[PDB]
Structure formats: structure tokens, C-alpha cells
Length: 212
Length: 209
Image 1 (cartoon, helix red, strand yellow):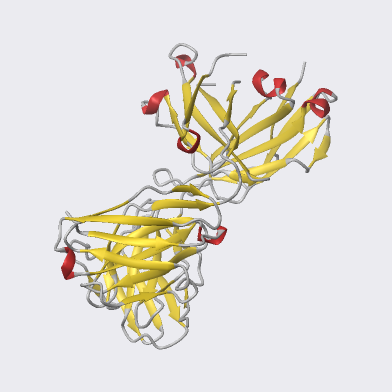
Image 2 (tube, rainbow over the protein chains, first blue to last red):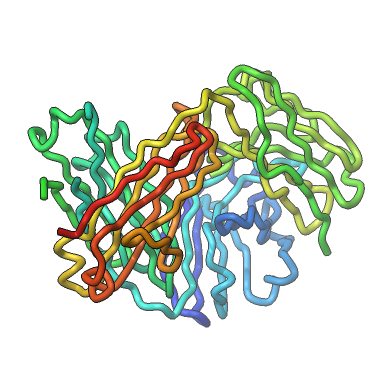
């Protein structure tokens, strides 16, 4: 299968520089135009740059032509994007894309998120939410930066009846909550634990929900 | 400089199994140099305005040329996806804003649950009261907080899920965040949900005692 894997993103300081790579597999890399497209949630998709078969002719979004450089090595089958003097506006998920001969993108990478910000990484506080034929439990995840956090219940084995809500930004700290609903006769009998992972701070917190 | 692709409808109403058409208008002539994608990373659907890639099923139909383009989807089912148009007639390539389908289903009252602050949070000096309003339809809903019977508007933060891709409902979280000081000065904390499924609001409350 055609496969595109972008390299590690994360949180970087304004004004810094960083180089993205995308490892291409499952097709003849030199037979296709390649491109970079980025997307900030709620604002849509924005084309950044593309490059010809042999790298001899790139094209850029002119507002970014001053700080971005697209490149490719068809011996290693990798596409690069070099970014300089990064601004907070460069915060987005960046996708590598295979460009068809006419100009569409028939394959996209998994995307990698870049956060350009001088706010400090802050681990989350995780608070339990404890209280018919069904019962609803929850976890409140407050005061973390940057996005994202990953919430699971019972290490992922409890997935039905879960609602994990979008995070809300408040004074450069994020908050979200997640609720899970189980049959009333199975709690507290069969334990229910929320797991909150925050890769940016290398932290994970597990809170088992118990009656008040 | 910029060709603008406008998808004016952020949401498009339909029902399970129906055919539906999504529209995309170019600010200049792009001929047939238009692509369509779906996205929860995007997946390519149609190129050259009307051509399907190998593996895209024929329930997708592209149409249009010049400035007016449409994507038609037959046998729509519950999903968590939007549809994006793109022009590649000239640099820079530009995308539409996206259109999400809304699936009709029977009206459903929310299940409302309220939770007091945890012992851990109070130790830190904060006090969040959380109210979940889960699995309701249609998406329009109102939540009101009351503290000792008095309506409270400051310190409330709401978050909404997208329409669930399996039961076609919506859910909402409402969190009232106070200081421990203010929280200890009052007794009754009430979350009130107003929904078209009833003329009387659903009231969940607790007393700090």
C-alpha cells in the first residue's frame, strides 16, 4: 500500500527552525510530485509547497516562501520541509501528500502536529467525577499545555458509552472532560478507571472512580 | 495570489440512506481542475471534477466545470466525516472550508448528570461543578446554572461533541468553575437543561452538605 510517514512534531519556541521529513513507501517515489499541506482545526486546509519529480522546480505559498524550503531525496524516498523563524501562526498539523500528475493529492500522510508557542509545558490535573439501570462516571482534565491528551477507560477495554469532549482553551491552559456510562449493577463491582496521557509532559495519570 | 473555493454550507441536512449533494464555488474559472476529499487525514475521492480514483465506490459522483462544482453522495450513512473541495488550476492550490452531513433521527431527551468538586481539586483551591448532557437530538439545547436558586453565568465553560457516527446523537459538557472560597459560601448547585423534547427543563442538583 502507498504509505507516507511524517517525522516527529511537537512544541517549539517562536523564532526557532525545524526540518520535517516524510518517508515514502509502496510506490515509485520519483514518479510523482510531492507536496506539504497544513491544517489548523476549524480553519481548513492550507497548501504550503510542492516539488517536481527530480526536485528541480519547487513551488511555495508566497506568504511562506520567505521561511520554508521543500526538498526531496529519491534515493532514500523521503520528502523534507525546512521551516525557519517559526511564528505561532505556523501552529498546525502538517501532512505530506502525493500529488497526482494533474495536481490532486491521492494519498496523504498521517499528519504531525507542530505547536509554536512560548507557553510552558504543563502536566494535567485529573479529577474523578463520582455520583436507574445505568450510571454515568467521569474524569475532569484541567490545566495542561499543549494539546493533546489521550483519555481511555480501563486502559482502552471500556470503549462503549464514552464521550470525551473537545478541549477548551482558558488562559493558555486546556481543560476537557470525559464521561462513561455503564450498567448500574457493574459499578463499583467491576472497577472503572480513566487513563489520561499527556505525551508533551511525559505524564500519564490513572484515576479509579469510587463512590463518595 | 488566491483563487477562493467557497463551500457556503458548513452543514448539510439529510437522512440515512438518502442521496445528497455538496456544493463548491470557485471565485475564478478553474475549468475542471477540482478535487474532492473526505476527512474525519483526508482521503481522496474525485479528481478532474468528475473522475473517481481506483477504489472509490460509485456512490460518489463529481459534477461541474468552470466555477460551480458539486459532490453527490448516495446511500449516506452515519459517519464522522466532512467533505472538502480543492482547486489545482493555479498556484497557490486552495481548499474549500468543508461541509459536514447531519443525519436525521428521532428526537431524544438528554441524559443529565451533575458532579460536585472532587476532594483533590478543593485541596488546590478550585471548585468545578460538571454537568453532562448526553445523547440528545436535535443538537439545539440550552443549559442554565443556578446557585442557591440564582442564575449564574460567569465561570461556565461548554464543550460539544460532533454528531456521533453510530447513534446520530449529540452530547454536551458544561463546567462551572469557582474558587473554593465562593463554593463554600453557597449550598445548592443546579444544572438545568432546556430541550425541545419537553417544555419543562430537566433539573439536576446537589447540596454541598
